[PDB]
Image: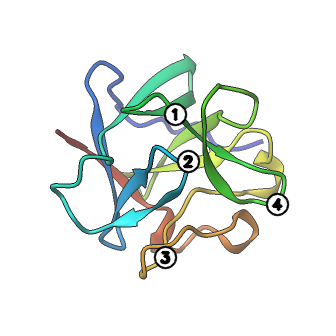
């Protein structure tokens, strides 16, 4: 029950998801998800892939998938499951945003705070800069 404005997107080469808050999304090997302003970090290289038109997976360099638990918390999973699917949509005509598929009706987006920590699903909404991402070349 959402719009269907899709972004160009590229699933062939890895990218660095940059947040409008000025942070890069990072997934550590131990499964911790957070944000960092260091462009030279080696845990921010991410790989995206299409599972359907509009649905995507966000995998890490080590082989972990970003996910969202029943409480709206983000974590890095070792194996893909129904919590690893995100609807990828265009926003503001230029940015990218990601909605949890399993919790789509509640509008739980992926976001980062200005201090570098993850936002919980229920705390996110249209109009905040924390949900606006931009995929850059590595």
Q: Position of residue 33 (x, y in %)?
A: 52, 56
Mark 3 vs mark 1, CA separation in Å: 22 Å
Residue 2 placement, left or right of 90 = right
Q: Is residue 94 visible?
A: no
Q: Residue 113 shows which numbered tag? A: 3
* Disc 2: which residue: 31
107 with respect to 91 (left or right): right
70 w.r.t. 52: above or below: below
Is 110 placed above or below 37 here?
above
The residue beneath circle 1 is: 64
Q: Residue at x 42, y 74 (%)?
A: 116
Alpha-carbon distance for marks 2 and 4? 17 Å
Residue depth check, mark 4 versus mark 1: number of the one nearer the observer = 1
What residue is pinned by disc 4? Answer: 71
Q: Nearer the viewer, mark 3 or mark 1?
A: 1
Badge 1 local density, few (<14 within 10 Å), some, or many (20+)?
many
CB within 8 Å, label 1 to label 2: yes
Secondary element type, mark 1: loop
């Amino acid at each position: 029950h959402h719009h269907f404005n899709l972004p160009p997107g590229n699933y062939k080469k890895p990218k660095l998801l940059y947040c409008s808050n000025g942070h890069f999304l990072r997934i550590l090997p131990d499964g911790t998800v957070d944000g960092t302003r260091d462009r030279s970090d080696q845990h921010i290289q991410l790989q995206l892939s299409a599972e359907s038109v509009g649905e995507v997976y966000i995998k890490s360099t080590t082989g972990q998938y970003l996910a969202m638990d029943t409480d709206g918390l983000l974590y890095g999973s070792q194996t893909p499951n129904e919590e690893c699917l995100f609807l990828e949509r265009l926003e503001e005509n230029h940015y990218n945003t990601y909605i949890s598929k399993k919790h789509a009706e509640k509008n739980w987006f992926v976001g980062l705070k200005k201090n570098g920590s993850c936002k919980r699903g229920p705390r996110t909404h249209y109009g905040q800069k924390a949900i606006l991402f931009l995929p850059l070349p590595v």
